[PDB]
Image 1: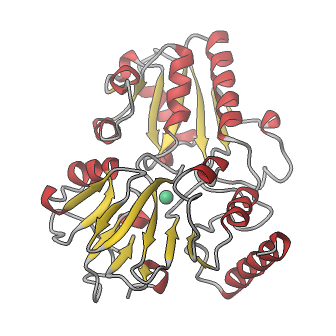
Image 2 (image 1 turned 90 degrees about the vertical axis):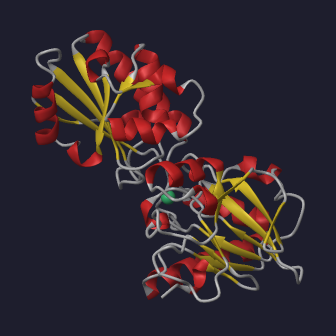
Image 3 (image 1 turned 180 degrees about the horizontal axis):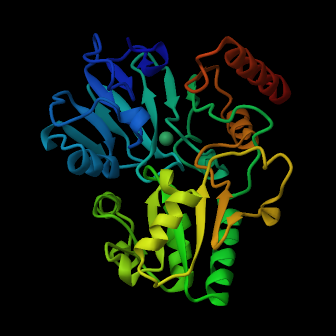
Length: 341
Ligand code: NI
């Protein structure tokens, strides 16, 4: 049955609640982004109204074959009316098409659901600045002070310089990047751009990327692997065995692989700076784990909530254990006492 933290009080609305069958009293189903833990349950047989971004609507239509008449895409940063309630969709700084949703309840309560997000000071200048929020449904993925990670910009600088160096030293090296969902496209696109190559990938992945409105994408991606020296493979194939096999398939065009695994966090963060990151190497294969996150660090999360000053916080992640929930509630009290709301 549907958890309480997916239900918006005083409305007929749910958020990211497609795996519970017909939810009692739900008149409109919102989808924050196209990740499987959130969309699980949608298909061509869904016949309730789904409200989402344009990009998410493209992916529903083309990848899951949801019928167009049930997809209701909304423009960002625009006041819209849904079943009698004003809503706004804001950029979540997550994966392409990912949104936060502001709901303006008829009784005067204002609710922000972040979906999945990476908090940023840029958010302090959207339509959030203009009114008070009473309740915050918060992505608490990394809600503990051990979770520090560098900016996206520093991580991409490290990747570009590493790949450019390796291929300049050996023009017969192949670069491989792992993927399992949309998100983190900057990793493989920035590398291809510095090498003057397109990114080669499966037809299924190319189709997924064509749904995303990324400008000049026909310019950076391709299904012709033979013309490309940056290849995208499933994340599960980013290991020594999987990569030895791929290299066999390239028919002696290449004699070395440098591969990247963009992870969220890994405990090498508590000790090591990005500058200090080293690969695992075996033979002519090296694998770098890089801490490219599309969720808030602890400090970014803290800053956002201390700026927003909500009256109540409802966590949406790590809610399944009493020790996690207690930990989070303790941090929320600290933040409130330190900031004075
Ligand atoms: Ni997500």
